[PDB]
Amino acid sequence: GVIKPDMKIKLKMEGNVNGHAFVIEGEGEGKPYDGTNTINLEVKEGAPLPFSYDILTNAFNRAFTKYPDDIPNYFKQSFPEGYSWERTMTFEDKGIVKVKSDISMEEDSFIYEIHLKGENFPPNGPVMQKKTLKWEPSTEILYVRDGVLVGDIKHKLLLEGGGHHRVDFKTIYRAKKAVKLPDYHFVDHRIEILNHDKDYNKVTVYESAVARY
Image (cartoon, rainbow, N blue to C red; front, top):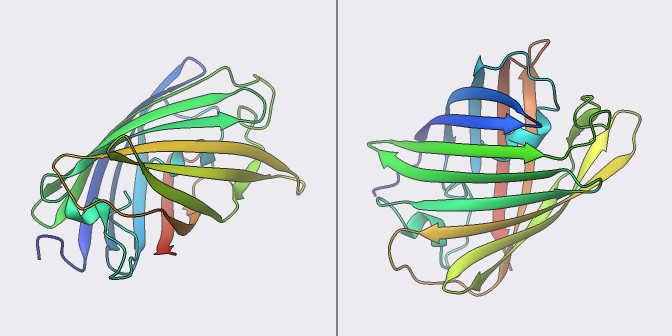
């Protein structure tokens, strides 16, 4: 196979949140057919980040999703050419993150080039004052729109103290060649920061994702 059962991950993100510019690079590995991936991440510019690292982690590849055989796999079919995605994250309190990523392949590695811009976050709200705990697990709904694939999620951040903040995600996935398109389906995922240093200059992220009817 062009996609191996064990794939490396290399990525760079250029981002700007509420006017604060930063660059993060990461290297990881995962199991595309098991739906798991792990990435080690270092802030290269812009340290220490003055906002919640959780608004970045979903940006750090649905080729790492476990799919049954009777649902066409839009992401894996796109390789070796790959695919790009554009995402909008609409926060409860009017903050917004717009992110784009290019996913390519180099031998047994996926390569991501990510650009992220967050703005209009309340300066003293939970994202900019780093009061998040994690993303709750959630379920993406995937379906074709306009020939490409769309993913909707109604997400929640768990905050310090136990409350939640809603965040709605819309992603448009665009394969770089014609692929067999799937009927609508769902992807159950979980994402976690496994470890971080004091200011999140060094972070390890883990995600698990499984498609189903």
